[PDB]
Amino acid sequence: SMSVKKPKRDDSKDLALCSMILTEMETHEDAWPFLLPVNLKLVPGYKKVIKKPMDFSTIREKLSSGQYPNLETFALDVRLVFDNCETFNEDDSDIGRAGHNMRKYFEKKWTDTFK
Image 1: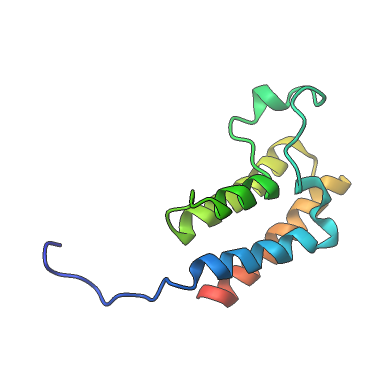
Image 2: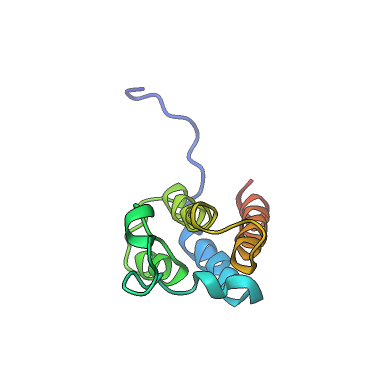
């Protein structure tokens, strides 16, 4: 509350560490469904169904331009990529499987880097 603060967690390396995690997600072999925005002219249903599209390149640009106020807003967009994937793709599809794999990969890196 006012003039009563918990001890200051050092957040000065968060930017660089989110960038490193993002690099590792970008270079994973199962990243291909997620690298670029879904083409809303060419994929029927996407525009109407997925209210907040998100992809790694869009996260990379937001990161690079100071549009994440903190590491939690970064994690929300990464998770949004996988939540969108599950909304639109069957679990038993290549893309559906890609999404589950990448989410697992991301969540371990997240815990190991910050928890």
